[PDB]
Amino acid sequence: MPSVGKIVLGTVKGDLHDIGKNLVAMMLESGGFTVYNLGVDIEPGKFVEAVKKYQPDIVGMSALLTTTMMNMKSTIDALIAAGLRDRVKVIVGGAPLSQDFADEIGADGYAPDAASATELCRQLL
């Protein structure tokens, strides 16, 4: 299937949940996206490395622990420090996530589920 975009996805530092993230990846691939699934417990600097390596259109972060949500902000800060923040759109999700939180940390988008995440990614491109 021709690639309609490139997406780097990971579960954030401190967090080992990936069932939801993996469903998001599967649904994104079904629409033509190239998805680089980094895995879990992904450090801010490893997101930065991935953006340099894969040159994605979008960076997506998943968190299921309330106590790991602020590592999404840490990752955004790392992207800013690396000079990469304007080259990518940042999306966040997970059961404890919300649009209000996405706004608070400076992400470009939030989606409540895998189906809506695919539409969000299409809109962000």
Image (cartoon, helix red, strand yellow):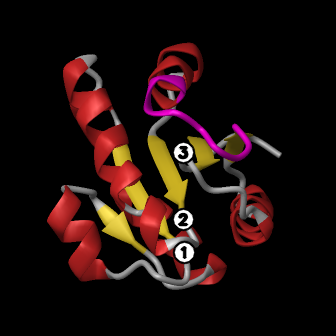
Task: Using the image, determine if residue 23 lies above or below residue 57.
Answer: below
Task: Say which quarter of the image contains residue 82.
Answer: top left
Mark 1 burial class by Cα count in 10 Å: few <14, some 14-19, many 20+: many
Chief secondary structure of the magenta portion: loop
Q: Nearer the viewer, mark 1 or mark 3?
A: 3
Up/down of 56 relative to 124, above or below = above
Tag 3: amino acid:
Lys
Q: Are marks 1 and 3 in contact (CB under 8 Å)?
A: no
Q: Report the amino acid beneath label 1.
A: Gly
Report the side of 86 relative to 109 (left or right): left
Vertical placement of 15 versus 44: above or below? below
Mark 3 closeness class: few <14, some 14–19, many ≥20 residues within 10 Å? many
User: Which residue position holds label 1?
Assistant: 94
| Three-letter residue code for mark 2 | Ala
Q: Secondary structure at mark 3?
A: loop
* 26 lies left or right of 65: right
Residue ID at (26%, 74%): 101
Marks 1/3: CA distance? 14 Å
Q: Which residues are magenta?
A: 38-46
CB contact under 8 Å: marks 2 and 3: no
Residue 83 rendering spot, x and y as whole percentages: 22, 18
Is residue 46 visible to the viewer in this orientation of the structure?
yes
Give the alpha-carbon distance from disc 2 to disc 3, as whole Å: 9 Å
Question: What residue is disc 3 on?
Answer: 13
Residue 29 pos. (x, y %): 76, 56
| Residue bearing mark 2 | 63
Pointer 1 or 2: first along the chain:
2
> Please, what secondary structure does the residue beneath circle 2 have?
loop
Q: Pinpoint residue 60: horizontal percent, then vertical percent.
A: 51, 52
Name the image quarter holding residue 70: bottom left
